[PDB]
Image (cartoon, coloured by chain):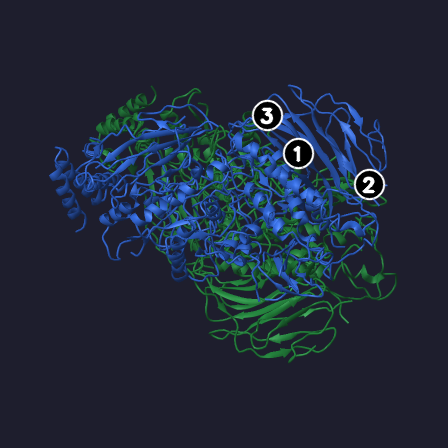
Chain colours: A blue, B green
Amino acid sequence: XXXXXXXXXXXXXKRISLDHDHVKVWWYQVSFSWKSIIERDKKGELEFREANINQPFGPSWSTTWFKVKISLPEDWVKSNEQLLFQWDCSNEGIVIDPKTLIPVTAFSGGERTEYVLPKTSDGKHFFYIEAGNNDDNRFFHLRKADLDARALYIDFWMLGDAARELPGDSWQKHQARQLGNAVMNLFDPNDRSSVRKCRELLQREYFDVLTNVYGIGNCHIDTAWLWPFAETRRKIVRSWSSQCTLMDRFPEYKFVASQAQQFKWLLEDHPEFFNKVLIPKIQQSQFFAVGGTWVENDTNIPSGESLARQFFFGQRFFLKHFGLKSKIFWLPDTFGYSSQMPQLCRLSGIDKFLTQKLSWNNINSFPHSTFNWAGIDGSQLLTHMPPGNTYTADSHFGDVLRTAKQNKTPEYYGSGLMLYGKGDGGGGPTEEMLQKMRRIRSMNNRNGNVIPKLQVGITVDEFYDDILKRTNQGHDLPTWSGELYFEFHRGTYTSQAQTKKLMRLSEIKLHDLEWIAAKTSVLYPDSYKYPSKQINELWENVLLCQFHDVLPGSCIEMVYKYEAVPMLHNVVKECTSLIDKTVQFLQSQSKADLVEMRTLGYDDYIVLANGKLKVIICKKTGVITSITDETLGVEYLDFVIYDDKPLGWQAWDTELYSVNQYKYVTKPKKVQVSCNTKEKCAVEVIFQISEKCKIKSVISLNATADAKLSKVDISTTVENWDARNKFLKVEFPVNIRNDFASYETQFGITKRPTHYNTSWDVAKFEVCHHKFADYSEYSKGVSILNDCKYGFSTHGNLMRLSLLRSPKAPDAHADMGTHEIKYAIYPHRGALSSDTVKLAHEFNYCFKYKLPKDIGMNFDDIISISGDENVILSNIKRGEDEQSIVVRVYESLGGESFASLNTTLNLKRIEKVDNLEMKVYNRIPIKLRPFEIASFRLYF
Amino acid sequence: XXXXXXXXXXXXXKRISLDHDHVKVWWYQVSFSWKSIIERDKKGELEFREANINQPFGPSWSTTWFKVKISLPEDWVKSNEQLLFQWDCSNEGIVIDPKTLIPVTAFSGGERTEYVLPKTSDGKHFFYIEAGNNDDNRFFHLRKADLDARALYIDFWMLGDAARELPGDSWQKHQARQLGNAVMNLFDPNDRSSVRKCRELLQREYFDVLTNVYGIGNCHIDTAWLWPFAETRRKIVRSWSSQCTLMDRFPEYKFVASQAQQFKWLLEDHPEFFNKVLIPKIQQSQFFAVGGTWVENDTNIPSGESLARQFFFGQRFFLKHFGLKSKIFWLPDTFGYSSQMPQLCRLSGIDKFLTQKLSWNNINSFPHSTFNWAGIDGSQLLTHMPPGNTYTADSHFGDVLRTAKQNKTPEYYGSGLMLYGKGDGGGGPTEEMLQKMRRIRSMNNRNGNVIPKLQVGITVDEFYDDILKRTNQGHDLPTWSGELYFEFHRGTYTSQAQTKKLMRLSEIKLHDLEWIAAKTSVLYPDSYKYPSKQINELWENVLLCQFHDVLPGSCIEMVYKYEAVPMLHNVVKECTSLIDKTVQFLQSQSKADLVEMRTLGYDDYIVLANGKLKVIICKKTGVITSITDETLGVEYLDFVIYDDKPLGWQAWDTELYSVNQYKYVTKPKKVQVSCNTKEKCAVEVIFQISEKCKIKSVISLNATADAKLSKVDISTTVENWDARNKFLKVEFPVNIRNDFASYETQFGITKRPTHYNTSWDVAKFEVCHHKFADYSEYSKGVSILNDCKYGFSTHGNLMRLSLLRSPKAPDAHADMGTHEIKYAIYPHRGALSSDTVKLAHEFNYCFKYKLPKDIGMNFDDIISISGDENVILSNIKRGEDEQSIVVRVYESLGGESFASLNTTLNLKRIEKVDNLEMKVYNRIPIKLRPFEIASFRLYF
């Protein structure tokens, strides 16, 4: 059918010319800054040397600079020709043509790329290019030219490619075939006069339901990944330069940036001439900042304060010369989404959101891609969702009509959605031939509006103007309550808990000193008292490791050591330095000060004797048998049984072997008890397994009301040895029947069933959590507190916490070494149903005691008339510039009770203020809605 | 490709002979019993007259008898020929060849059918056949014959039909084509010698992974449907006779019967010779009784007592000569299934269940058709599920390989499942050519076991022996918690509430006198005291209208009048007669007796002033604005707003018009108040709509602690007029956020979300309920009590009760006429969370007061030491034969608390006994499991 005759023939087979200049070429390498090397160039004879040939290398962390001094050949003849220099793209680097140094040019784009030499100025210039190693040898040759001949070659390549994508039943496929025919006729027998003429004839063969197809070129950059931050800091400057050279070459282009800190990275590295580059670039057009967010992160693990700073400290750039923005919120690589996001968005002045994964196309009780998200708070979020092709559809895309068809099926709207650029790497490239892409697509389809029109230059702001018109304001709409569920690729989330232990301890610790440091305002006045400039710098370093890829611990071994480096550590070390600092001139009013933040036995007979409860491990079995309440009457049989099953997948996802029996840790145990006291009781029982390894958990608790508490504390200490690729968990089967699982999400409590959605794919079902998870019919249940482990699962009502994971990924630090784990099991009652939530989250508190000399009185309870047990205040902090402070509260128990808010203060005034710390004229609500975040601001 | 050459040719086109006997033929009709007409035949000249021709008719409820006296033609020649008489099947009737009357023969089979004349006895006999009218004229002609020639014609017809079903890619399709070729060769030119010879040649062309394909011929009969009970009582005797004549013709055949009462219907109508027919039939083989159930019904609407009697009173036949049974439970036409069924099955000694609808094939978190059902009680149920082809796959099936392929995909097992016979009609037919069906399918596939073997004679009992072997005992298995959800065809469930009002009032009323009538045992001894024989006859009539098709009210107009007839009415009338009877010699110990069963204002300012709560309707709007708790703090905005939307579908399913605006009942209302008192407060507000109709609801409640109660009572009285095809509902939006909806199912409380499963198809989502439905985060919520309406819906947390429905089905009584409706709205609190459930269900109680002369003392509280608020005792009754009584309890609140059971009695003993009232040796449990039915028995 002549299918392989037209397609594979001409696609393979003045005009393009290749000249070679061997001399004047220099090479440089550092085996030990662009401004530092410019002074080391002209002076004497340094490591800069003549290359003139291909330079091989070997694996190193070193970077290799390269210098090419080119003299323009002849005068007029080769000037009209297009000047070009081809380079082989290495792992990283930069390219410059500095005098002395004005420019910064793009590198990080794909292995194929073009560098244009200015035809405006006739003379000799210089070139500075470095190549990051990880080895990749560069192929460098000068390439002259024509533009019209190469255009036809590209247009034909995108022609026949579009012929294959078009339906064979349509006449267009037979048309495009005949179009690929006539072109091949004059193209074959090597004729320049025919090629240029045939290009004109092809255009004549080209030009002879309201819908729209658009796209926005973007670069998604991970600040920490298998390449480090310092190296990727050089990678982000390559993303800006590719646009700058594209602007003069092509107009109407659109770029978006998920990092507000990206601006600062460029302003710190290139403060001089590139601060004045951004202003005409951003203000006029062609640039948009999405979300104005300081960090792109997973929202499940951290608190709302992490989401509070990124909005506020990312809005700080708006105070500088900046501020052309968009209403879209972009978290493409983020796994999972919080249920408080619809509430956080509207308050942050951002009305749109984008989600890559976590969706399906079918009747789900859900129509399509485009979606209006209604959280459990009751608020609504209009969000724009890309199809199942994700962001890799338009990434490095020359295929034209290929994914255009697959985009139309999931989406209805009046139009589709395309995201240009790659989100996997040091940063995404932006192709320079996109100008022809938009043009050649306007060659196939006619102009005027009848058939869908092709415009790549439209902005999402105008796109959101279209959705406000076509579709109704709505009452009954696409509706999904809570979060979304698809293949999560949880992976490292529960793996390498040691980086969580450091972070989660640093999380609370940095969240510790915040508010109380504003309570010393009255004591010693200067600015009064608050580490405004001091704590601002603190949040700068912490948010850097909190990114979506970095925080769970999925990365190479090099940057993983930078996670356990002072980056995480010194934060705790500086905060523990400040907490011992501010105390000196403060606590001096305290003789003996207990510092805590709030606002108002037997062996053979196997018993630990007390009133509250009883939990018993059988003899020689090693497994807890009876957990039973006398007053309640609930008896348990199948507790705390540790289970170890291997893992055969990589760091990304988790895939267990087919029907693999999980090895129990039960063995010929021995019995022991740590101490002897009414205050302290710890009974020790040893567990062992094949390839002997010591797995230790501890038992701690306070009796009743001599010790006082309602909850046990069980901490696990395990030093891993030998066998890798294993996944360890501890089971807490409730032996109870409930279709609902109580779990506390970020700023609230979400309601999720015991069984996953019927559309679920992956066998293994695990859920990420903050602190505790419960099962409650409201008259009773079982509550499980935990530390350093964010994961858990619903087994058919068997509570299983994930202690450790060891992926087969190329990381050797995820396998062996000691670990300190902690968790708990708590008895549940209807009266204690609101108590278990209160005794869970903030239990991470660490007791600390210190005393100065005595002059004063140390008892002051300064909080004013609120007293709501159903509400919990997560964050209260100051401002930037005044020093007005903000107060943010959220209701713990919601969905049933309507919390009356009497919260107020004295000696000053108060007004309700959103999460962006921006002034809002409703006033303080006397009653809080269920599952509502209440944030306020305080002024003198 | 010669596809239509072989298939449509020979399929259309001594041997078959047609003779006509005009004389000796008689006809009979009753325009005004088989035993009554036999005495009216030979005597004188009655309405029995000579027919000899085709007799036309007209629509009537009459039945037309027919008599054919046939003399055997010649002697030997036409004796060897197969004697047959063809009849045109009418709506109903019976066929007999009585001397004087021995036989009863089958009729109700399809319009085509065969009646064989005995070749054993040479002589003259008689024929008695009646035809039910609803007119259908009968075509009657005597047909002689051969058996070998007709066999080839059938075998060839099932051959070419199997050729089309077989894949064209396989050689079998090309083979069967060539098989259809050679046969057509000798068949075409009218040769008897060739046909008989070619039949032998075809058999030679026939005969030349472990799996099994089986089936069981069955007849599903609805006792009340578009044809009445008295008429279908004649229809059930036609189902038995078709088997009896089939037994001698073909062996190994299997029949099953979902009705245990079906035996009694035959024993009452034919007590003499047909009581001795069943014993060799059932005992040896070929017959199985499924479930031993008295009735086949919807389990959602009635109580457990209805499910208790059907097992017990259906097990009464086992006491007679009976009792070859099966472990399968069959409810094919039943819409929806209870969650207590896994618990009820194991106790009833029945380990298997069958479900037609309510399933899907995909990964649902569910593998396949075959399923092990785990209820919310924790118990497991192994159930056998037919594919998506339901029971109509093998119904009237000559198509052979057709549905054989579609059966294999949903099911894995080692084998598939097929159900022969039709479940829609007066009763299902069983074809007589099934003998050849099993044989011809053994002609295509070889014998011995390699390929799947075809046996239609295997019993499900042996089938359950295979499932115990191949598959594992299991831990992780197919798992679905609670009920199942697919297209329900709710329909008449909420339509025609008047038949529910009569039944639901009769439900409780018949459930009333049961236990307390055993409490008078000591008073006047004879047998002591209990209506053992009296209340047994009561349950006989009531269960008759409780069937799955009859109870919801989906039926013709004729039997619908039989629903409102004394059948439902006299039950209440006889029970209200007995309650005024037994009182006379009982209550005489009571001077003044209050009889109840248990065991221990303003207008312009628009307010009804009291302490407990406040509910306000705005002026002129007609809609309730603020329902607010002061102590709790929950304020409501959007209550009790009646909504009317039309309906464009039939009685079966419910389909609303595409985006049709539901008309509000708001209008220029006027304000009024019924009475004036602290005891009685009713404020009246009128509603009206287009084509004016008076829609009235009432307001009743008791204040606090002069009136005392925690709950309002709102009863609706509406007389329908004019416009039909409408669906009326009243909305109670909570204005709250909950992912869970609290609802009390039969014997317990099931947990269902606010959103339907993602695999749901139909837009409109409505749920059937018993009494109340709630939404609880356990600290608060909203409780809705209702009467006579079993339906409700979850709108995104808007409570909507269905008042009335008017389908477009051919029933004129579902449209107009008055209706009395009642419901309620209740305030919810954590402490009252167990109270709302207690104040909901049994509120249907009706106050009654009567007094006799005074001698005695009327206060005795006889219950002994239980006192569990979380448990509720639904039923306690006596036995059959002694007169030992049984006690059945079930826990209301479960899934959280483990209820300690101290329940016991005095002066006698007690033992745990299952739902079948059969003696069980665990003893009385001291603690009850969550969601567990506890049934016991009491002996002297």
| Mark 2 element type | loop
Mark before the other along the chain sequence, 2 or 1: 2
Mark before the other along the chain sequence, 3 or 2: 3
Q: CA gap, disc 2 to disc 1?
A: 24 Å
Percent x, y of residue A93: 41, 35
Disc 2 marks a residue whose amino acid type is Ala
| Label pair 2/1, CB-CB below 8 angstroms | no
Q: Is residue A793 visible to the viewer in this orientation of the structure?
A: no
**In the image shown, does B226 or A864 lie closer to the viewer?**
A864
Where does label 3 land, which residue? A661
Compared across the picture, whether B188 is left or right of B138 comes to left
Q: Residue furthest right?
A: B856
Q: Tell me whether marks 3 and 2 sit on the same chain.
A: yes
**Chain for disc number 1:** A
**In the image shown, does B915 or B408 lie closer to the viewer?**
B408
The circle drawn on residue A703 is 2
Q: Residues within 10 Å of mark 1 (few under 14, many from 20)?
A: some
Percent x, y of residue A151: 22, 42
**In the image shown, does B697 or A745 lie closer to the viewer?**
A745
Disc 1 marks a residue whose amino acid type is Glu
Compared across the picture, whether A551 is left or right of B682 comes to left
Where does label 1 land, which residue? A731
Q: Residues within 10 Å of mark 3 (few under 14, many from 20)?
A: few
Disc 3 marks a residue whose amino acid type is Gln
